[PDB]
Image (tube, rainbow, N blue to C red; front, side, top):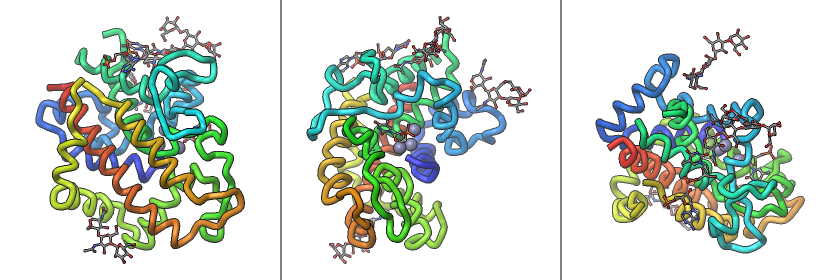
Length: 255
Ligand SMILES: *[C@@H]1O[C@H](CO)[C@@H](O[C@@H]2O[C@H](CO)[C@@H](O[C@@H]3O[C@H](CO[C@H]4O[C@H](CO)[C@@H](O)[C@H](O)[C@@H]4O)[C@@H](O)[C@H](O[C@H]4O[C@H](CO)[C@@H](O)[C@H](O)[C@@H]4O)[C@@H]3O)[C@H](O)[C@H]2NC(C)=O)[C@H](O)[C@H]1NC(C)=O
Ligand SMILES: *[C@@H]1O[C@H](CO)[C@@H](O[C@@H]2O[C@H](CO)[C@@H](O[C@@H]3O[C@H](CO)[C@@H](O)[C@H](O[C@H]4O[C@H](CO)[C@@H](O)[C@H](O)[C@@H]4O)[C@@H]3O)[C@H](O)[C@H]2NC(C)=O)[C@H](O)[C@H]1NC(C)=O
Ligand SMILES: *[C@@H]1O[C@H](CO)[C@@H](O[C@@H]2O[C@H](CO)[C@@H](O[C@H]3O[C@H](CO)[C@@H](O)[C@H](O)[C@@H]3O)[C@H](O)[C@H]2NC(C)=O)[C@H](O)[C@H]1NC(C)=O
Ligand SMILES: Nc1ncnc2c1ncn2[C@H]1C[C@H](O)[C@@H](COP(=O)(O)O)O1
Ligand SMILES: Cc1cn([C@H]2C[C@H](O)[C@@H](COP(=O)(O)O)O2)c(=O)[nH]c1=O
Ligand SMILES: [Zn+2]
Ligand SMILES: [Zn+2]
Ligand SMILES: [Zn+2]
């Protein structure tokens, strides 16, 4: 996701932390964050080049189908097993269980960002179009690629048009639905019979890529109201799942 997506996810997560996780997060965040996890939930994107090894950890590539399997798909272009967003979640969650040889501030920042990214449907999608990056279309009147539409445009368009430029408006509406509309689902979202369950989230993601993101889109299309309104609920779902799961995972880790 772009900035707004990670902010929403980390804001949702922050308020669902239990006291032990809230305390550990306070301790692990730098002072410049002023205690706000969401202030640093894009940090991982800002070290993709400084930490060149980290770039493939933001996503998963699959074959041209609607399935994901860790052993088959979790590797980078070099073929190194584990080097995908699911593997990264396993890695950084395991490190945080120690709360060495590792910088656990980075571990927290990585796991927070990656838990978000693994919920972006096109972050678990086809190698053949680089997760929709090579599908060039228009978002209303402006040129955009499909991946960017999912990272940013849908959310930014909702933020402006539907929420009158209040990002807290979308956070608040998601939080209300988590409590009053999706309560049974949320309990399932939180449940993990391991510390982290990223393969569940990736499998949902590739299915969404097939059924919602790629669905109906061709090179050169103009995506506007029809696509926007029909896909917004899935974006809401994934952001909500991301926040709920990030909190549940941190709670398990620090508890
Ligand atoms: C789990 O989380 C950890 C912590 O963030 C990640 O650890 C990093 O892993 C990468 C490799 O995947 C490391 O980067 C590589 O470092 C090599 C040498 O690093 C030495 O120093 C580190 C400590 O900083 C020690 O582990 C040890 O002393 C190492 O010997 C470099 O040689 C590599 O660069 C060269 O090869 C690459 C391609 O392979 C080229 O692109 C480069 O240009 C260069 O030629 C590379 O930089 C990194 O150092 C690790 N950091 C730490 C703190 O340990 C894991 O990757 C992560 N795994 C997941 C998520 O799956
Ligand atoms: C655990 O990991 C975290 C995250 O990587 C790390 O915190 C980071 O520390 C660095 C370096 O200490 C901070 O970057 C500095 O920011 C200050 C702002 O006050 C600048 O003054 C610094 O600039 C100088 O140093 C640079 C060094 O390369 C020079 O290039 C530059 O020209 C200046 O001389 C520097 O940018 C960074 O802000 C934090 N990041 C976060 C998110 O807090 C922490 O130190 C690690 N813990 C360890 C190693 O124990
Ligand atoms: C929070 O949950 C709210 C209740 O589910 C939801 O409001 C509802 O949003 C749906 C769209 O998902 C609207 O349903 C629309 O569905 C048909 C099918 O295309 C449309 O043709 C209709 O016009 C219909 O509006 C509901 O009307 C709407 N319900 C209410 C009471 O306003 C919110 O969108 C959810 N918000 C978040 C952030 O998740
Ligand atoms: N198919 C499959 N499922 C899950 N994990 C896998 C799989 N293949 C390899 N691994 C790795 C991923 C983690 O690094 C490690 C512990 O996962 P843990 O699940 O925490 O024991 O096992
Ligand atoms: C290459 C690639 C990038 N991405 C993501 C990472 C970034 O969010 C965005 C752009 O990355 P890029 O600038 O390296 O192409 O797309 C995927 O989801 N799948 C891919 O196969
Ligand atoms: Zn992202
Ligand atoms: Zn992206
Ligand atoms: Zn990212």
